[PDB]
Image (cartoon, coloured by chain):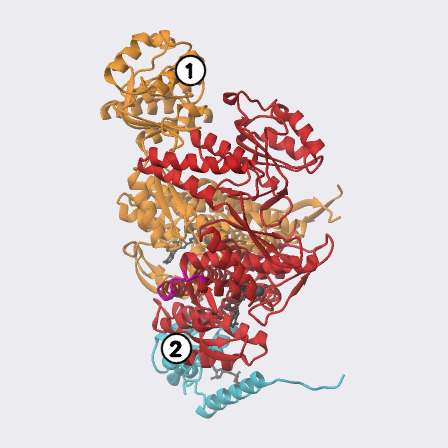
Chain colours: A red, B orange, C cyan
Amino acid sequence: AAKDVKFGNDARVKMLRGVNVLADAVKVTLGPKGRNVVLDKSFGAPTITKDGVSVAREIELEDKFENMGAQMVKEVASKANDAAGDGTTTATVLAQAIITEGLKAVAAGMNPMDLKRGIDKAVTAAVEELKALSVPCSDSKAIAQVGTISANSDETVGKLIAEAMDKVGKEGVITVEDGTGLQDELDVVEGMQFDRGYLSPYFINKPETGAVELESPFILLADKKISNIREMLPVLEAVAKAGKPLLIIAEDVEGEALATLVVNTMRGIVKVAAVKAPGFGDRRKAMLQDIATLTGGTVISEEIGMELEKATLEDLGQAKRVVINKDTTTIIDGVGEEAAIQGRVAQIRQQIEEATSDYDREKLQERVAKLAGGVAVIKVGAATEVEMKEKKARVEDALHATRAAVEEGVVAGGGVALIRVASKLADLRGQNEDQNVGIKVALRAMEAPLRQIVLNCGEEPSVVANTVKGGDGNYGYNAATEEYGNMIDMGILDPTKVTRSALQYAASVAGLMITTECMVTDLPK
Amino acid sequence: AAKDVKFGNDARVKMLRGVNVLADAVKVTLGPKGRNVVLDKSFGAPTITKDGVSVAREIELEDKFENMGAQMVKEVASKANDAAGDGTTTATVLAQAIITEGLKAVAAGMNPMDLKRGIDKAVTAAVEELKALSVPCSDSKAIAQVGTISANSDETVGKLIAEAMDKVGKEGVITVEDGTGLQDELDVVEGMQFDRGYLSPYFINKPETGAVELESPFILLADKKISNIREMLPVLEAVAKAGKPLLIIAEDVEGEALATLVVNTMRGIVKVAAVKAPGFGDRRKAMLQDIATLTGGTVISEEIGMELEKATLEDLGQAKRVVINKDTTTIIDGVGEEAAIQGRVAQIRQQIEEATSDYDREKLQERVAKLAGGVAVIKVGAATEVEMKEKKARVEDALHATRAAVEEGVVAGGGVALIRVASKLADLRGQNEDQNVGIKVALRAMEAPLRQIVLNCGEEPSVVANTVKGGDGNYGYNAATEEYGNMIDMGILDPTKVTRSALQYAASVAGLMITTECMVTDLPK
Amino acid sequence: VAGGGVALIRVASKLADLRGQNEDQNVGIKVALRAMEAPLRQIVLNCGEEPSVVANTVKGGDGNYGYNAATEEYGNMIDMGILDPTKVTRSALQYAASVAGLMITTECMVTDL
Ligand SMILES: Nc1ncnc2c1ncn2[C@@H]1O[C@H](COP(=O)(O)OP(=O)(O)O)[C@@H](O)[C@H]1O
Ligand SMILES: Nc1ncnc2c1ncn2[C@@H]1O[C@H](COP(=O)(O)OP(=O)(O)O)[C@@H](O)[C@H]1O
Ligand SMILES: Nc1ncnc2c1ncn2[C@@H]1O[C@H](COP(=O)(O)OP(=O)(O)O)[C@@H](O)[C@H]1O
Ligand code: BEF
Ligand code: BEF
Ligand SMILES: [K+]
Ligand SMILES: [K+]
Ligand SMILES: [Mg+2]
Ligand SMILES: [Mg+2]
């Protein structure tokens, strides 16, 4: 197709307009006084959301150049969401800040390459500063706060996340699903997380988020490589009569089979997923039988006297719910054989005492811990499915923030952290003036998230900004109460991870963009 | 379909406009202050790229005739990138200048074909002059420089390429792939790789490793479909007396032979790896004999007159270690003597001179390359996908640059080489005054790269040009720091190949383009 | 003063050191200094000489060294007698800057249909 081509300022102006039209839509959601965006997902009812990445992802624009700028920044939000839960709106605001300031500086005629280079220098130093600044978060209390604040000041959500991580342990798997009724509920259930994802992205169905959730999935527990579903087509027949999805957990699935699934599942009877049998060798057979007990199934191989041709409804495992993602699968609540489950537990422990060689102790300890943790599930309470999505999303942000916190701990939230580091870096300089002004752009931009958060209040942004700067250490602004104080004591806790991630990815993309003189895009008509 | 046809200046003017549009898109990227172009990739995030040939490919214009101009200059860009990875932008700028000056000379009424001949004559002399200027590049430091300069002054990248080329020697294969961390990382697949592996899991003695590794393995090089253990009996005796494992590089992983060798592996009597022979037919045979001599063995098959019983300890190959994978084998320090290995490479070089078909040419080069050393892999570290692509492209350019440098030497970069050769050629003349004009056209265009590099800096191009021309030898302009000096001592090194290649292709396409009198294209409907 | 735009470009080179309180004032200063070269380059371009080379050569010269557009020779403007009154240069510059400042600060325009 014939390409339109633009140069210099025309390109830059087009870009910047597209950026703004995305950012402004994202950034309205920021902080405690942010407010919701309505996304008209064609399928049905619109979804009201406060998640910035959910907003950004939808934004697509009519002008090919403005759209190009928008799609570019879109990347930032998705990256941040892929590192961490929170931080997608902060990362977008930072990116748009750098871009704006940087383009201003380029209009002064300064070299964009050196501008980019200077931004990168600042970010590196900034990241280092945050690291040192971060106070480890380990007190359940602090964990709660982190939760709460990521939940948009939702006390109850913080409570539940803290209690769940207490009950399963901080390393334990926790999951969130549409609850049955009005109230939030928490319970711990017999389930398993093993580190294998979908064997193909074509199994991604219901969620957009690169995952699949299946209700009452059947589990074919076969330590074999599936060449063609012919080997179990009467099982898929059976499963048709079920009308309930089948999870293959097998050593491999050939693309022949995968393509046959593509031919028959969504285009036909029932959705089917395949996952790699976890671990390897004797371990993988071990885990498959560990899951058979967890699900009341059997291991399907001729070493057992079983065959893919023969596995009954009852030779396959039964789970109530399974989640699969790019990298991991969580059997949420296997039917299983509870007494046998516990007996297995005791058995595996005995091998810890027998298989006392260091790495055997390790694997066995892992497996017992895995089985003993089970899984927690958080049931989101809502009157209406609209609020279901909204609250559920708010919870998952809390969840991902808490784990991130537990990893790296917390820094003074509300954007104080970024300002603080900014102030520390004021003496940082580059090789040349272009890099020096690039550094100043970076530092400057770090202000943006505070100002934005204030602005959403409709408080007077520059005033708050200036005072906070005047303050020192943890001194910040509480935007839910319009009071200066020790942010920590208030519990406005940001996990260093999210802030670090947001800054890196924001600068990363931003620095590139400024350097553009020319854009090649298809003529609209 | 009904063709539109235009003549004379209605043709050339339109054609030139197309050329200009493409060039201007490309040009911006030239040099250290050259700056990125955003190429829309409708399915995905746009590609931010500084690779000029990447730019060229996308350019395509609505106006049929302007399109023609673009399409033909596009061709020189691409051809440049085929000959050598770097130099695509230089070739474009050159082509633009020649075309521009040629069309101008034609407007004077010069015989176009004489111009073309004059251009061609000048170009030939310039190639010879570059050959004369070129100083061998050999020291690692120069390699680093060339890599740096081609990397867009990315010192780290130059360092990494140079040390990688050292670790695997000049002739080693080096490849670049998407890393995961922020930090770039270099790995090497040690030893004699060959690209065939096991086709069952039961060979794996190291299940946590997920591959088969053997220490002090003997190597039964039976390039055949092995049948039975019976033929191995005396071999197995010698093996068991040595107490060493055995690598079965069969033709194909087949036969009861291997099945019972797996049985012996499970009994711990002898541990055995088995893999396909690489390639087919005579080239398959050749690889097995190359493995053999390198391993200090000899191809143990009846098709070369030796039944498997007949193998001495000079026919069985050995290594300190071997590893075999799903798809690949590597042999670590085969016991074959270094003199035998070198000699074997000599016969392979004789075979290379005998080979007249890519089926054997590329494969023979791969044999000698792997015999010279392992394969290095450069993992490009970047925060963001956009960086992934952008950084990767620069790395790849650096890689192909260094290669070219090693093979043909280097000249003073920043376009000084072209300037110098142009000045040396000022005495050249043709058969007739039309031809002489064409020569001067060529010599004048040689300035264009230098000027364009300067212009991107926003510096007076002709001022810099004149001062450079006034200087002698490697005296030039450093566009990264805006001061003149010995270009070589600064380390701004260009591979002669890329300079030479870029010039030739530029000249060829341009010299044709100026002789256009009529263009025929479908009407715009 | 050296008439041939020499004076302006001379002073422009002299003041390159000057800098302001912030990037906005710095770009403003740079804009002013760059413009002052414009007379010389225009005069030359009318000749169809290369403005860049002549400008640089004048800048690299000293005092009244300048480009005689009538003859294309370089020389001392005074010896040739290419004399601008000082007032003319000064007034030209100041008034030019005045309008520019007016225009930059201009926020609204009112006219009939
Ligand atoms: N009560 C509060 N006072 C000040 N800042 C707050 C408060 N509650 C939340 N914030 C800040 O708002 C941001 C969280 O809002 P959110 O929309 O989740 O941003 P993101 O999507 O980037 O996580 C964090 O910077 C957090 O510190
Ligand atoms: N520091 C420098 N000073 C001057 N010229 C440079 C410098 N670094 C690189 N160059 C020049 O930049 C030119 C263009 O390089 P590049 O951007 O890779 O375009 P191409 O695709 O033609 O190689 C090269 O001829 C190189 O000599
Ligand atoms: N021979 C010459 N070479 C170069 N510059 C000249 C020459 N003669 C006059 N000038 C300069 O040309 C400039 C502009 O000329 P002109 O446009 O006629 O005057 P003004 O711009 O004041 O109306 C004057 O500043 C003058 O000194
Ligand atoms: F704005 Be986010 F996703 F916390
Ligand atoms: F623009 Be290139 F390939 F250096
Ligand atoms: K938000
Ligand atoms: K380039
Ligand atoms: Mg948040
Ligand atoms: Mg290059």
Tell me, for residue B133, which label it has, or none.
none
Q: Is residue B524 above or below residue A280?
A: below
User: Magenta residues?
Assistant: A132-140
Give the image quadrant in which the ligand numbered 2 is located: bottom left
Does dot 2 land on a helix, a strand or a loop?
A: loop
Image location (x, y in percent) of residue B117: 49, 43
Question: How many residues crowd around disc 1 within 10 Å: few (fewer than 14), some, or many (20 or more)?
Answer: some
Chain at numbered mark 1: B
A345 inside magenta stretch: no
Give B448 or A424, whichever is nearer the viewer: A424
Q: Is residue A132 left or right of residue A259?
A: left
Residue B411 visible (yes or no): no
Chain at numbered mark 2: A
Q: How far apart are marks 1 and 2 (CA)?
A: 74 Å
User: Mark 2 is on which residue type?
Assistant: Asp
User: Mark 1 is on which residue type?
Assistant: Ala
A139 inside magenta stretch: yes
Q: In this view, does B453 lie above or below C34?
A: above
Give the residue drawn at x 25%, y 18%.
B243
Instruction: Please name the residue that numbered disc 1 is placed on.
Output: B259
Does dot 1 land on a helix, a strand or a loop?
A: helix
Q: Are marks 1 and 2 in contact (CB under 8 Å)?
A: no
Residue A37 visible (yes or no): yes
The number of numbered badges drawn on the structure is 2
Quadrant containing the N terminus of chain B is top right
Q: In which quarter of the image is residue A69?
A: bottom right
Image location (x, y in percent) of residue B461: 43, 64
Instruction: Please name the residue that numbered disc 2 is placed on.
Output: A472
